[PDB]
Length: 393
Ligand code: HEM
Ligand SMILES: COc1ccc(C(=O)O)cc1
Ligand SMILES: [Cl-]
Image (cartoon, rainbow, N blue to C red; front, side, top):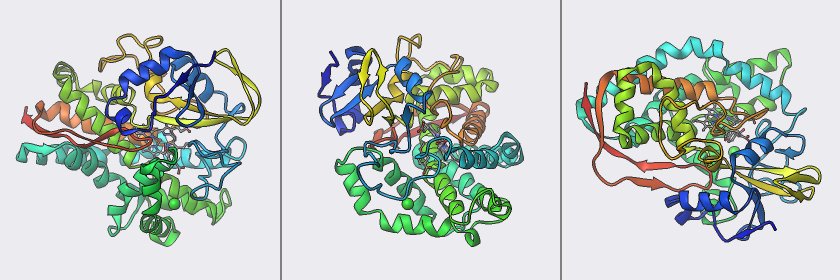
């Protein structure tokens, strides 16, 4: 019954061309058994969406990577939000939700939009740019660290620190073991910046620490919640903006549609998150025996969810392999779904929308011109280099 697959969804060969293996994942059955990591997988939209939306049965407090925190020591002290279940999750979730609320976004949106317009104007002076280094990375680096209230020095650690955190969800392969062996200087940098004296007034970090004054969180919790924004808040949006530029470069007809109606910017960014799914996978662990995909899975079992595959599952999406900036994207799982659904999603959408808006208004063509190089990571999907030529409007 439950079919076996030898597919290693954490291997270099899979990252370099995942779609034929994702389709085998889906077609083999609603639940698969991965022999490479002795773990159950669900790759269809129906199972992934159901598991995200039953956190009681499929918990996050035993870890959302392969490692079971009941059985093995976590590689770092657990996140208070990502690796917690309700009710322990609920208070820190409510705190970060207020820190990153629609009201907060309104207060920072003009400066984010101005930085994205200035960036696109500067890139158009050079013409030949790397859409990763000069855009997908440079743009969030120019707005997010400042929005957090970080000091200038040490910011070069932010991307490798996120790369470590996202590799650490994976199985114990070489990407994970190498990242953990090199982790100490990145972790020392982030640990210092999570402290209250180091976070400038008015930014997200100081706003988090302001909740210690009323007692909503303790002095020990506050630096761990700042740590969640420094683990997830930059490299995700780097890879989301990168996906969107890549999609627009490969689908020239969709770029023209966006130029013809720039109000499509926010949806063209949502559709890039669905299409590429920058965060490809998370796990859950069962807290009871449960029927999943017609099979009775025992209590205590890891289940790997393939969010990228759910987002491309033809049982749910029409022409899922096409980038379509007017697709109805509501329901995609690129930001997760339910109680843990991305608490930073308004920040990611803000950055995505204002950058795509600047591109829609200022650029007439995006042509790939030189070797595209993939970056490999156990959880994040994206490119290391995307050289392009931008033609001004
Ligand atoms: C395109 C960009 C992004 C993508 C694709 C993404 C993806 C995800 C996904 C799939 C989850 C669900 C985790 C789960 O169910 O276990 C999540 C949660 C989370 N995200 Fe995002 N994210 C992005 C941007 C951001 C940003 C900008 C921030 C912060 C400023 C952020 C902070 C977090 C945090 C702290 C959680 C844990 C929420 C919880 O457990 O309740 N993310 N995100
Ligand atoms: C979506 O990826 C992450 C990674 C880490 C954290 C965290 O450290 O809380 C949250 C979400
Ligand atoms: Cl850490």
